[PDB]
Every structure is written in structure tokens, then in C-alpha cells.
Image (tube, coloured by chain):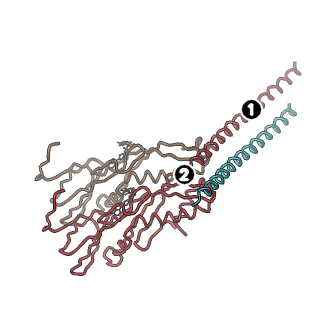
Chain colours: A cyan, B red, C brown
Amino acid sequence: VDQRTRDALQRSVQLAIEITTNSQEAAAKHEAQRLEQEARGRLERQKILD
Amino acid sequence: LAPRNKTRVVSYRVPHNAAVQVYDYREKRARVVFGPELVSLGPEEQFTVLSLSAGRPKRPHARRALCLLLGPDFFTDVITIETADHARLQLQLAYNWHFEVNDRKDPQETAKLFSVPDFVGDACKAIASRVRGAVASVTFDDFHKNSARIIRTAVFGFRDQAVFPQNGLVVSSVDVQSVEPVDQRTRDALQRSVQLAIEITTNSQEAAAKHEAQRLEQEARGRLERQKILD
Amino acid sequence: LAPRNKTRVVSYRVPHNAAVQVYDYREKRARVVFGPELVSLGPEEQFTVLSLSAGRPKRPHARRALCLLLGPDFFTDVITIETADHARLQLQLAYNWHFEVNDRKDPQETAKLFSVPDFVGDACKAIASRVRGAVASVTFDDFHKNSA
Ligand SMILES: NC(=O)c1ccc[n+]([C@@H]2O[C@H](COP(=O)([O-])OP(=O)(O)OC[C@H]3O[C@@H](n4cnc5c(N)ncnc54)[C@H](O)[C@@H]3O)[C@@H](O)[C@H]2O)c1
Ligand SMILES: NC(=O)c1ccc[n+]([C@@H]2O[C@H](COP(=O)([O-])OP(=O)(O)OC[C@H]3O[C@@H](n4cnc5c(N)ncnc54)[C@H](O)[C@@H]3O)[C@@H](O)[C@H]2O)c1
């Protein structure tokens, strides 16, 4: 019945959306770091072979 | 239009896959007429007029009719629900139904098609209550990624069809059409999510290109050093 | 146009790969006429008019017709979907269909072609629900590279 209550719940749903976007950005950052380290390791082994 | 002749036998042509109910108030005898037969009233018989539901949010008392069509039709309803994350969002569903009349010669089975005089509003509010109840304990992300299975489990049970045994109305399918948030801020927040996904994809292709460039650069450098020592 | 002679036998020429349904309300007998035959009504027979779906987003009740064409045609629909990355994007699809009539002499099989009086809106919303449901759990990059 109270409008303030519904307005308070809108902040809850926008915080849930912000949480989901932060989660996908963190997953992308960790995949980027894994590929970066794999390429760096292959590059170092190739420099020693050269 | 033009007036009808009150002295002529009042009659009506029942379509294919339809039925009418008509009770002889004098001779005390009911009959349900199926198929594409032509129905002609006796001197004291009357029709059973069906007050049905229609419209886009399925309001009641919106389509009065005279015969009952029991074919594989569908009707579509708009359902506003809210999730466990308090995400208000509205749906558009589609409901394949038909009537299972086992025997058309049975006076007791075929009477039950008119046992429920608003077979559309009943089924639509029933499926609305079921879907609304099951989604209210499901978060927004799970619902967005799995909303076919959620609603198909909410409507049916533990089952391929949702039979309604008061009148024999099965519901054989549900077809979700449009799921969008009621709140504009919600949609605006999701636009930032999709543009971040695109930026992630471009950063991934740029990193892959950089690592391929570094591999070719080191290979050429190694061949150059071996050639300088040979010279 | 010019008025028709009400006293003449009302008749209609069914095309190739088509059918009509017509029920004799007096003699209590239905018949489904196939092929390119010419159909002539008895004194109490009537046609079954089909209210179909048409248009670019496939609205309902947009093309009333009289005979049923059961050939290898296609109809095209526009489907707005959304992916697991919340990418709203619309499609244009094309649906090769035909009717499988095993026996044209069977009164019960051939009655079922008119069992569903809007065979276009039904199939298009059904394929819309299926595609919309399956793509909603697939990310945007996978869908763009593998959407066939
Ligand atoms: N198999 C199919 O896919 C199929 C077959 C026939 C018709 N259709 C059409 O699909 C459309 C869906 O639109 P909607 O439901 O959003 O519009 P709506 O909500 O206004 O339709 C109300 C529903 O009530 C039903 N109805 C009306 N009068 C009736 C009677 N006398 N007896 C029994 N049932 C009756 C109709 O079939 C319709 O589906 C219908 O208008 C219908 O003509 C589909
Ligand atoms: N094999 C083929 O590729 C082939 C064959 C014939 C026609 N076509 C044409 O392809 C076009 C596709 O356009 P669209 O579907 O976007 O336009 P649309 O969506 O307006 O067409 C509606 C569909 O309903 C069908 N239809 C109309 N009246 C009918 C009846 N009485 N009985 C049975 N079916 C009926 C038509 O075949 C058409 O495909 C059609 O207009 C059709 O003429 C293709």
C-alpha cells in the first residue's frame, strides 16, 4: 500500500543488477589473466629455445 | 436489421467442432447438439447463452456467444509478475487448449462442458496464479536464463498436459512470447550490461592479436640472431 | 460488382493443390473436395470460410479465404528475441511447410486439415516460442557465430 516501500524495493532490484554485472566483469578479468599468463609462459620457453 | 418472422421456426447453424446446449422447458428434456448439425428449436426450447472472457488483459464478460467451440484453439493473456529480487515484469503467454469429449452420446459427460460457464477466464486466472506463484521464489538471473522451463514446470505438474476435470478442458502447451520489465530503469541498467559484454569481447580479440604479434616477433628475432652468428 | 443470379447453382473452382470443406446441413453429410475439381453446392450446403493470419509481424485475422492450399509454400515471420547477455535483436525467418495427407479418401484424416482453423498463426507463434526460449540461455557471441 505504501509507495515508500515500493521505492525501497526498486533500490534492491538495481543493486541485484549491479551485482550481476560486477560478477561477469570479474569472470572476464580472470579469463583474461589466465590467457595472458599462458602466452607469457610459452613466450619464455621459446626465448630459451632460441 | 430487418425484423424476423416470429411465427417461423427459430433455428441456428452450429459450426464444425462446436456444440450447443438446449433444454425443452415443456417436455423436460435437455440435449447437447454436436458437430456441424443445424439446430431447430421446439416451441418452448431455449438456448444457453455463454458469457465468456476476452480482451488483451482478459477481462470478464467481454464476448457473449451462443455455441461452444471445442477445437484446438488458443488464447493469449498478459501476466504481470514479480520475482524474488522484486523485479516487476510482464509476460505474454499463449495457451493451446481443447475439450476432451470421450463420448458425444453420453448425457452426463457432455453436460459438463457447460458446467463451467466461463472456461477462458477460469483457465487464464489459474495459470496466472500458478506462474505468478512459482516465479516469486526464483531470482531474476535464473528466470531470465531459464524462463521456458520455469513456466513449463509452473503450469504443468508431475506432465505433458494440464487437464481441468470440471469441464474436460486440457491445456496442451504454453508459449511465452515477450518478457520485459515494467520499470524503465531496469531496462536501462541491462543496457549497460550488454555494452560491457561487447567491450569484453573486443578486449579479448585485441589481447589475442597482441599475443600472436609477440609470438611472430620473437620467432623472427631468433632466426635473425642465428643468421648473424652464421655470417 | 454486378449482382449474382440467386437462382443459379452457386459454384467455385478449387485450384491445384488445394481443398475445401462443405457440409450438407440438410442431408447430414460432410465432404472434403481435393485437387483442381470444380465444387458446386447443393441447395443447403455451405462453405467453411477460413480466417487466417498474415502481415509482416503475422497479425491474426488478416486474410479470410475459402479454399485450403496444401502445397509446399512458405511464410515469413519477424521474431524479436533477447539473449543471455540481454541483447535485444530481431529476426526474419522463413518456414517451408506442406500438409501430409496420407489418404484423400479417408473421411477422418481429411477432416483434420480444418481441425485447426488458423494453421499459420499457430505454427508461427509455436516456432517463435521455441526459438525465443532456446536463444535466451545462449550468449551473444555464440549466437552470432552459430545462429544457424
Ligand atoms: N490452432 C490454432 O492455432 C487456432 C485455431 C483456430 C483459431 N485460432 C485463433 O487464435 C486466436 C488467438 O487470439 P486470442 O485468444 O488472443 O484472442 P481472444 O483472447 O479475444 O480470444 C478468445 C478465445 O476464446 C475462444 N472462443 C471464442 N468464442 C468461442 C465459443 N463460442 N466457443 C469456444 N471458444 C470460443 C477463441 O477460440 C479465442 O481463442 C483466436 O482469435 C483464434 O481465432 C487459432
Ligand atoms: N515453394 C515456394 O517457395 C512457394 C510456392 C508458392 C508460393 N510461394 C510464395 O511465397 C510467399 C511468402 O510470403 P509470406 O508468407 O511472407 O506472405 P504472407 O505471410 O502474407 O503469406 C501467408 C501465407 O499463407 C498461405 N496461404 C494463403 N492463403 C491460403 C489458403 N487459402 N490455403 C493455404 N494457405 C494459404 C500462403 O501460401 C502464404 O505463404 C507467399 O506469398 C507465396 O505466394 C512460395
Parent chain of label 2: B
Circle nearer the viewer, 2 or 1: 2
Ligand 1 sits in quadrant:
bottom left
Q: Do discs 2 and 1 share a chain?
A: yes
The spot of residue B147 in percent (x, y) is 57, 56
Q: Quadrant of the C terminus of chain A?
A: top right
The spot of residue C25 in percent (x, y) is 20, 64
Q: Quadrant of the N terminus of chain A?
A: bottom right
The numbered mark at residue B210 is 1
What residue occupies the far top of the structure in this picture? B231
Circle 1: element type: helix
What residue appears at the point 27 percent right and 51 percent down from the top-left corner? C66
Characterize the local packing of mark 1: few (<14), some (14-19) or many (20 or more) Cα atoms within 10 angstroms: few
Residue B219, quarter of picture: top right
Figure check: A40 above or below B28: above
What residue appears at the point 24 percent right and 49 percent down from the top-left corner? C14
Parent chain of label 1: B
Figure check: A26 above or below B210: below
- Amino acid marked by disc 2: Val
The spot of residue B59 in percent (x, y) is 41, 60
Disc 2 marks which residue?
B182
Circle 2: element type: loop
Figure check: B200 above or below C26: above
Q: CA distance from mark 2 to mark 1?
A: 43 Å
What residue occupies the far bottom of the structure in this picture? B28
- Front in this rendered view, residue B149 or B62: B62
- Amino acid marked by disc 1: Lys
